[PDB]
Image (cartoon, helix red, strand yellow):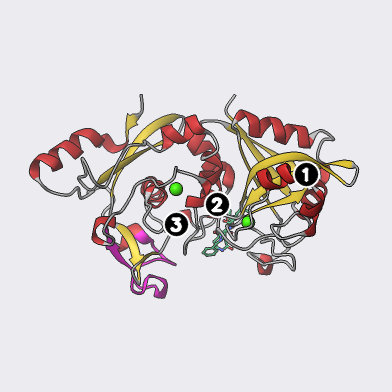
């Protein structure tokens, strides 16, 4: 079983608050400026203007922990440079066993609610159970940091808060490497591929890793500080972590074409080239494969041919449990 982070015992704390008729207040990570950050999100920073702390039960009538599953569409980046972490969370949702360890299902804002939630994180070689109270940073009535596409779903906001807590602040998460999130969610180890010097069986490696439930991510190198977050003509984002979420071969124009699916953790802004949501390539695939694979939705998720993926992306990471 998990070690209790800072000795905090989720069930004992929840039970005490429920018996006291009160809501949990986390003395280890309070709703104070220092929990937001120290410089860019520091006390005298314009970027913290109007940010307040509110529980979901102070925001909406029927807040939910999980709605329609804990899935990758629940991961929509906010105003914090933690794309690496959010790509890791989205990839985690594809591994059902690890997802249910990291995110204890059954926590609720209704029955048994006492303003306290918990998550499991892999930290310094061990699983640890991290509690948070459910006060979250809000500006203009909306979550400022990660949020779900479902406006009344909070498991991912609370998971990001727990990750901030073990790092001391939200700002501590701004700028990072996806491998750290992958490993902190799985206990596995990340292998890095330079796509210019990829083995000839990389596609099969990707297929098998997705099938096993490994966590995969990819990115485009920057050439200078100016390329950071630059949006290309075909609406890829440079210096930005993507989740690799699928891979399938389809019959197309008399050949077998290998496709790969990835997801921008913004939850919006997608590739516009071949195999994009509205591209003409789907006209020439099997109608069942078209129905199984293609979703016409601005959700950050899209397909590319493996050939285009190797032309446009620079790096791939595969975090295997093994
Ligand atoms: C990511 O694209 C993101 O969070 N975008 C939304 C956003 C951007 C800016 C402000 C708020 C929200 C980030 C964006 C950068 C981080 C924040 C500061 N300015 C940015 O452009 N991109 C990263 O975090 C990249 C992602 C990695 C993923 C693995 C492959 C390489 C790119 N990482 C860094 O920028 C980074 C990583 C590390 C590690 C150690 C020290 C410093 C550092 O910086
Ligand atoms: Ca959901
Ligand atoms: Ca899409």
Distance between the Cα atoms at labels 1 and 2? 40 Å
Q: Are marks 1 and 2 in contact (CB under 8 Å)?
A: no
Residue at the (78%, 45%) spot, across then down: 195
| Mark 1 / mark 3, whichever is N-terminal | 3
Q: Which residue is mark 2?
A: 176
Q: Residue 121 in magenta?
A: no
Q: Earlier in the sequence, mark 3 or mark 2?
A: 3
Quarter holding ligand 1: bottom right
Identify the secondary structure beneath mark 1: loop
Q: Which residues are magenta?
A: 36-55
SS at mark 2?
loop
Q: Nearer the viewer, mark 1 or mark 2?
A: 1
Q: Pick the residue in front: 318 or 22.
A: 22
> Left or right: 172 with respect to 206?
left
Residue placed most toward the observer, 98 or 64: 64
Q: Position of residue 55 (x, y in %)?
A: 26, 57
Q: Is mark 2 within 8 Å of ligand 1?
A: yes
**Is label 1's Cβ within 8 Å of ligand 3?**
no
Mark 1 or mark 2: whose residue is earlier in sequence: 2
Q: Residue at x 27, y 61 (%)?
A: 54
Where does the N terminus fall, quadrant-wise? top left
List the residue tagged with mark 1.
Answer: 286
| Pick the front one: 145 or 302 | 302
Label 1 CA crowd tier, 10 Å (few <14, some 14–19, many 20+):
few
């Amino acid at each position: 079983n998990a070690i209790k982070y800072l000795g905090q015992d989720y069930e004992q704390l929840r039970v005490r608050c429920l018996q006291s008729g009160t809501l949990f207040r986390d003395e280890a990570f309070p709703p104070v400026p220092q929990s937001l950050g120290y410089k860019d999100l520091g006390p005298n920073s314009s970027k913290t203007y109007g940010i307040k702390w509110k529980r979901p039960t102070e925001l909406l009538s029927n807040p939910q922990f999980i709605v329609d599953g804990a899935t990758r569409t629940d991961i929509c980046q906010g105003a914090l440079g933690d794309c690496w972490l959010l790509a890791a969370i989205a990839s985690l949702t594809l591994n059902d066993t690890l997802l249910h360890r990291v995110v204890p299902h059954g926590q609720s804002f209704q029955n048994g609610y006492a303003g306290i939630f918990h998550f499991q994180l892999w930290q310094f070689g061990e699983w640890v159970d991290v509690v948070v109270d459910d006060l979250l940073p809000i500006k203009d009535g909306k979550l400022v940091f990660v949020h779900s596409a479902e406006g009344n779903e909070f498991w991912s906001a609370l998971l990001e808060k727990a990750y901030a807590k073990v790092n001391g602040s939200y700002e501590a998460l701004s700028g990072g490497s996806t491998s750290e999130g992958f490993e902190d969610f799985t206990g596995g180890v990340t292998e890095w591929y330079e796509l210019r010097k990829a083995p000839s069986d990389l596609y099969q490696i990707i297929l098998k890793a997705l099938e096993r439930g490994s966590l995969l991510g990819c990115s485009i190198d920057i050439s200078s500080v100016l390329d950071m977050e630059a949006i290309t003509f075909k609406k890829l984002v440079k210096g930005h972590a993507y989740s690799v979420t699928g891979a399938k071969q389809v019959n197309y124009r008399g050949q077998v074409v290998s496709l790969i699916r990835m997801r921008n953790p913004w939850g919006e802004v997608e590739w516009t080239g071949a195999w994009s949501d509205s591209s003409s390539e789907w006209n020439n695939v099997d109608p069942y494969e078209r129905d199984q694979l293609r979703v016409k939705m601005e959700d950050g998720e899209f397909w590319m041919s493996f050939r285009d993926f190797m032309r446009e992306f620079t790096r791939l990471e595969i975090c295997n449990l093994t």
